[PDB]
Image (cartoon, grey):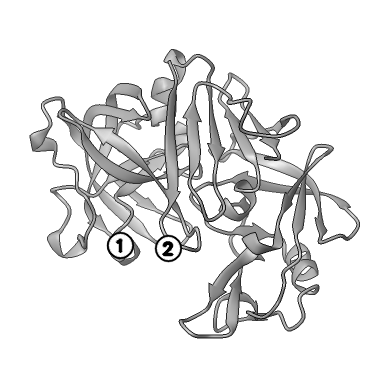
């Protein structure tokens, strides 16, 4: 089997991407944030504290003839940005882009943190990291991809995120028309439960490529590119007037600037992030200070190849017995 679904930016900055997901019978379609940095499929629901729901579409398990309470199971998750959610668990039929999994754990939120409530466009998350990170207790549950894998034509999914435009998540096949050149594959460590890999270096604009190993994770659920402070300083040094602002929370730059590109290495291959992808707009409405899309990972404890990096590539998440990642230009 295969599936293919369009993923759409939630706003004009590509802060996140939402993909429609069919849950239950009859289908209830919710728009979920596909997150290769986590492993829970959780949704706003009829059980979510009413004051914490503000415009999201909810899953109502009592209206699904295939929903079953997973007795005794609870979940609770905290994300790298400080947000969190928790609740109980149902199993139900879940379909993405025509690919159906029966008996998928659907984690129904009883509580969500304020950042989720305040984002009316995201109805929940669909985790695509390794199932070892799933938070359901006392019986850990499998991700949608883990459940689908054996049925897929090939045990892979691909992320093709758009810049200021929709893109595609495919399951079970590699669309050879969706990228240019060849896909370069690189080794993955699953020891932390992430799609963790090692970039071979970077360049700023038209500058020389610096060969250096940068361990990090491919994370579709993180907006920005978080790299070591040395790398980030080298980038922003090429933007007149850019500086790190402790009060804003990262590097800012004059909105009048033209940003240089940023290149990262995948083996001997190179992925070029155009400068425009690194502009996250005014820090507050009407400001002439703009927020940068490349930020330091110091204090996060891991480097993160988030959407800024991934949307410059066609990315293969190869879930074979020994997983690997592939990157192609597009």
Q: Is residue 23 left or right of residue 299?
A: left
Q: Residues within 10 Å of mark 1 (few under 14, many from 20)?
A: some
Q: Residue at 48% of width from left, 50% of height from top?
A: 221
Element at label 2? loop
Total marks shown come to 2
Quadrant where the image shows the C terminus = top right
> Which residue is labeled 2 in the image?
82
Q: Is residue 231 left or right of residue 285?
A: right
Cα separation, mark 1 vs mark 2, equals 9 Å
Mark carried by residue 113: 1
Q: Given the current orientation, which residue lies at the most extreme right position?
A: 208
Q: Residues within 10 Å of mark 2 (few under 14, many from 20)?
A: few
- Report x, y in % for residue 76: 31, 49
Q: Is residue 119 visible?
A: yes
Q: Residue at 59% of width from left, 77% of height from top?
A: 290
Q: Is residue 287 left or right of residue 93?
A: right
**308 or 305, which lies in front?**
308
- Report x, y in % for residue 54: 21, 63
Element at label 1? loop
């Amino acid at each position: 089997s295969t599936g293919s679904a369009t993923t759409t930016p939630i706003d004009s900055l590509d802060d996140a991407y939402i993909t429609p997901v069919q849950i239950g019978t009859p289908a209830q379609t919710l728009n979920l944030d596909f997150d290769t940095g986590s492993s829970d499929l959780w949704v706003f629901s009829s059980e979510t504290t009413a004051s914490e729901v503000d415009g999201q579409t909810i899953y109502t398990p009592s209206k699904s003839t295939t929903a079953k309470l997973l007795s005794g199971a609870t979940w609770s998750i905290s994300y790298g940005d400080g947000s969190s959610s928790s609740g109980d668990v149902y199993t139900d039929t879940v379909s993405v882009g025509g690919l159906t999994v029966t008996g998928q754990a659907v984690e129904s939120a009883k509580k969500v943190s304020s950042s989720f409530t305040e984002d009316s466009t995201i109805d929940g998350l669909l985790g695509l990291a390794f199932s070892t990170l799933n938070t359901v207790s006392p019986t850990q549950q499998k991700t949608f991809f883990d459940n689908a894998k054996a049925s897929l034509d090939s045990p892979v999914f691909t992320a093709d995120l758009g810049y200021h435009a929709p893109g595609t998540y495919n399951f079970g096949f590699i669309d050879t028309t969706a990228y240019t050149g060849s896909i370069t594959y690189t080794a993955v460590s699953t020891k932390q439960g992430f799609w963790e890999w090692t970039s071979t270096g970077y360049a700023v604009g038209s500058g020389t490529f610096k060969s250096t190993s940068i361990d990090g994770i491919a994370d579709t659920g993180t907006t920005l590119l978080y790299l070591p402070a040395t790398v980030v300083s080298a980038y922003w040094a090429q933007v007149s007037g850019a500086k790190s602002s402790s009060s804003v929370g990262g590097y800012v730059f004059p909105c009048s600037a033209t940003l240089p590109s940023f290149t990262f290495g995948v083996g001997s291959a190179r992925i070029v992030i155009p400068g425009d992808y690194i502009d996250f707009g005014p820090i507050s409405t009407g400001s002439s200070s703009c927020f940068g899309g490349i930020q330091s990972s110091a204090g996060i404890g891991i480097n993160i190849f988030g959407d800024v990096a991934l949307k410059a590539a066609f990315v293969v998440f190869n879930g074979a017995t020994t997983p690997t990642l592939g990157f192609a230009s597009k």
